[PDB]
Image (cartoon, rainbow, N blue to C red):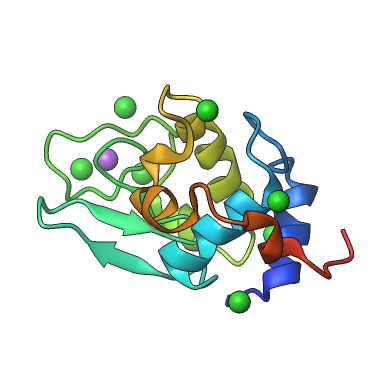
Length: 129
Ligand SMILES: [Cl-]
Ligand SMILES: [Cl-]
Ligand SMILES: [Cl-]
Ligand SMILES: [Cl-]
Ligand SMILES: [Cl-]
Ligand SMILES: [Cl-]
Ligand SMILES: [Cl-]
Ligand code: NA
């Protein structure tokens, strides 16, 4: 599924991400824009052989099981394929665990490089939330 900007903002709010660990909804929408372009089916292989899955590009190295990432963990206790669903529940639940892990949204390198410190409220501007 390819979400619209306000459509995803609304879904993220419905699943309790807005202001989760103090990160306003525009931070989460900005992260999703640069990680996946709002596409739930986005996948990207990392040089180390791990893979990033879904709207928030969650990595098989730590967070999900894809059966092909040696020495990895599955801390969200999910198959990485669950992160590609049109329903964002599994991605949101796993993202809440990641952002609680100690470095907040810095875990998302695209958030640190493209969203951090910017006018992230622009991402929810005009949205009926
Ligand atoms: Cl957009
Ligand atoms: Cl915001
Ligand atoms: Cl594995
Ligand atoms: Cl594990
Ligand atoms: Cl599995
Ligand atoms: Cl959803
Ligand atoms: Cl933080
Ligand atoms: Na894994």
